[PDB]
Image (spheres, coloured by chain):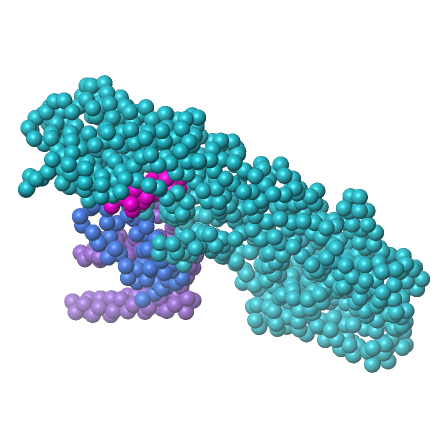
Amino acid sequence: SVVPDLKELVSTEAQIQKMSQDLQLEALTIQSETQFLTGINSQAANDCFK
Amino acid sequence: RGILLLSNRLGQLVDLTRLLAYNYETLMACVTMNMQHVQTLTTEKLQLTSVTSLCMLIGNATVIPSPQTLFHYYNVNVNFHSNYNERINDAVAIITAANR
Amino acid sequence: PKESILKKLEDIKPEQAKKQTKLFRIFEPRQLPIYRANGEKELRNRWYWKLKKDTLPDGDYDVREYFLNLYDQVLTEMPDYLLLKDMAVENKNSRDAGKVVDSETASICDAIFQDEETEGAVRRFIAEMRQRVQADRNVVNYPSILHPIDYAFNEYFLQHQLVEPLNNDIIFNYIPERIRNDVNYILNMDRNLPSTARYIRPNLLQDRLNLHDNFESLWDTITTSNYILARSVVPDLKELVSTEAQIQKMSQDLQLEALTIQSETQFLTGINSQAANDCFKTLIAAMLSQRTMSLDFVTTNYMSLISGMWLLTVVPNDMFIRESLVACQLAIVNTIIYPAFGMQRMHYRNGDPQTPFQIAEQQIQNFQVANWLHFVNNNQFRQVVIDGVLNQVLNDNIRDGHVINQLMEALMQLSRQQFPTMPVDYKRSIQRGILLLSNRLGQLVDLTRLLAYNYETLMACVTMNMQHVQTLTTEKLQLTSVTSLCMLIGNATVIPSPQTLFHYYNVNVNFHSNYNERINDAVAIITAANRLNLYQKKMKAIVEDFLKRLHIFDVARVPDDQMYRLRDRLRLLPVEVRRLDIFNLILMNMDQIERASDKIAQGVIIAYRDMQLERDEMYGYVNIARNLDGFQQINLEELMRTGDYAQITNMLLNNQPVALVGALPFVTDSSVISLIAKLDATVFAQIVKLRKVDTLKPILYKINSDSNDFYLVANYDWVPTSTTKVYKQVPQQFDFRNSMHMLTSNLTFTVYSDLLAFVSADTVEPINAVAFDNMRIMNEL
């Protein structure tokens, strides 16, 4: 109830996108799309923080 | 490659440390109840999901506890305490009487 | 899109000949009444200096930032060179025309030359004040009036003119030191440059940013770019065995049938009148740009593999990604060489990492086979530096470059494994494909030559010191096309059109120039940004613009991170004389500017004790101290920052002699009264109520019993008692005679852009071209 909410974050989309460029996601490895359920960060961080 | 994203950002990750450092170190100040470290019976789920986000995802942001906010906090624990202590007395008093 | 990142490239015109007109001044002289001690207006009036545009703000911080913008403005207007023929004007007076410099200069003269000035000496001077030319040196002499600070500027602008000469020889010299030398080409020009030539210098220092260490993301984007650029060049192949014909004899040599399949899967290789051109281009750029590609094969198409061996013998494996060389080799090793060389036994078991070609080397014996292995395996790029200036070219092992005893050996080794075996038939289909390389080997010898040259040619014109890392977008290449190019070529001889080559140079050039330039533009700012304590102009700012100015990069689509790290490196970078040399100038006088000009002050004192006032001429005599000698202080900037510790609050409450400092709003009053009433002590109270101040408008008392309808007091006899004066220097006065300076420049210039164009480039007949060995490239009928 107290822990101040955060502000000025990096656009969700922007980062995750440079992320795929860097991440080399789908490169053989079978167990895809489990590292990107990361999203809702604009939230997740606030939650993780509090 | 992933590791690097921690590193570059590291210049900022720093910022995180400072943040908490302060906040906890601040808020805390206004707690009357003592607090011995105990192995609670219950947990609290923390998805590395969010964690990871906070991490590479924080900019030159800077937030802290609103004055008014802080007090409100003190105030509460306070009352609570007062009640605990008080009832305690109210309690004891009776019980002892109850005996003689 | 494919050719949507190319229009963002060829459309980059960084070559901008920056020039100027208006002489850069900041303060125009102006009128104002004279107030002799005693305070009367003695008439005649005098001329002083006040700034054009008092913009200056409230708050030391806002001030500092303001100047900063000036720096940005200075640079964007930074005169790349000068010339005054274009600055003419006419003196209304003098021994004659006179032609002076800049309208303002003119005005002023005519002006003073009427309003009863200091007489003679002035009018006089204004007269025998003119121009004069010393043709013999191209020099020019023009008179000009400015201000110590003005001569200051304009001066250096003259003593630096980033414009050198330009003789035939220099043009010749800017044509890559390995092309003028390459025989196969010729050059010729249609004109003889005048002694009046000039040329700008596209500067191209190295990646002062080592954009490859950690930033991979960006390299990939560069490579890509540099790559497309290359294809745009890569010559389009010529005449090669009509598709149908070859593929037809192809079916023959092998012996086909009905449900008896073998070689049949080695023909989705047909299309080459598309594949060969693609495979060809693709290969070069890859190298040049230095991009890393992948591999799309099939385990049933062995032919497609054979050709692989063609490839691999070439491009030093490191050029291909890891997981690709891995597949490839093992596929060869386990289905082509062991399996029909009675060496099967163990169909070769490999379980990831270490090197699979390699290990086959130290395993089986056979010389022919054995040389291939070492030459291929340990084959790499020759990390070469200088090439007629820090080109830093990754080169191809002399050997390969046409001294293709590689190909001949690659074939001899193939001519000798086709001896032993195991699964009866299988050998039929495999060795038959192998032979198709051998007959063609007369021509294969060629393909090598081609690339050899091309890459080795195009090369030179890449000031962008390319290196050797790992891409991350991995361009895709099929053994399909490869295989096509291979058997389907010969007789032909192709080469880089002149015009083509230049165009290439030109681009990288600009680009470079931009990179280097923005870099300087970048640095300059940042450093300035520091000796200014702007703890609030959060830099996420500069980086952004920077990147943008070199289109290609989708700014919004790139995180804050990398960006900072980008600053971290920039910070350690030296500025450039030009850039630097100017900032030193702005600061050095900074003070002087601020102090002068109205709308602002500096600070105020509060001595709770009656006291005198200076008797300056400009203003009547008022509340001013140019020293604040003694008393204490308190930076306001740090105050409203820190949050005020009632330190001030207390002193104000208790009344103690004190001073204040920083940007401030002055306020002029008249009716003496105000003073006797001591109004000036009021104002302060406020603060007490509001921790912060800006609502603080201090007071000044312009007192000249002349214009102050309340002279009633100047009467008796007096002498100005005040409590609290103001920190603010005094607008200097104007000494014309000296105020003027003299100027030098040049007459009739001749600036040129682009260059090159001045040459008609021709080419020898294809049939007899030459490589770095003086041998006819393409000598197999």
Magenta part of the chain = C271-291
> Which chain is purple in the picture?
B
Q: Residue at x 17, y 36 (%)?
A: C302
Q: Residue at x 32, y 44 (%)?
A: C277
- C469 and C134: which one is in front? C134
Name the magenta segment's main secondary structure. helix
Magenta stretch: includes residue C280: yes
Quarter assignment of residue C624? bottom right
On the image, the x and y values in percent for residue C571 come to: 52, 46
Instruction: Give the image location of residue C739, x and y in percent.
Output: 82, 57
Relative to C678, is C144 above or below? above
The residue closer to the viewer here, C125 or C699, is: C125
Report the chain shown in blue.
A
Q: Nearer the viewer, residue C465 or C251?
A: C251
Residue at 85 percent across and 56 percent down: it is C130
Q: Provide the letter of the chain coloured cyan.
A: C
Q: Is residue C84 visible?
A: yes
